[PDB]
Amino acid sequence: SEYKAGDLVFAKMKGYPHWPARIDELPEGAVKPPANKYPIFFFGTHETAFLGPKDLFPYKEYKDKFGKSNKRKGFNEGLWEIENNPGV
Image 1 (cartoon, rainbow, N blue to C red):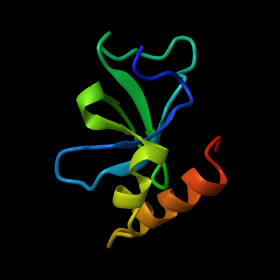
Image 2 (image 1 turned 90 degrees about the vertical axis):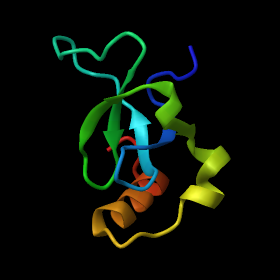
Image 3 (image 1 turned 60 degrees about the horizontal axis):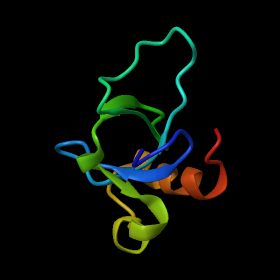
C-alpha cells in the first residue's frame, strides 16, 4: 500500500532522469502490471510503463532535488504538467 492511484511521483527508468509522473488508474480491461508494480503515466510525454516501488519517489518530497529542467523538451513539459494539469 506504498502508493495509490493518483499519487504524484518521480519515476525512474534506466537511462533517463527521474521523471515527473503519476500512479495511473488503468481503464477496466487494460492489462495490469505484475502485482508488485504500479501503472505509471509519465507527464510531458504521456508514456506508460510498469514500475516497482524502488523506482518511485513521492513528488513533493523529492521535487526540490529531482524537479530540475532537462535537455529533453518532454521532460520540461512534464514538470509543467505535474504542476498545472496533473489530471490530464
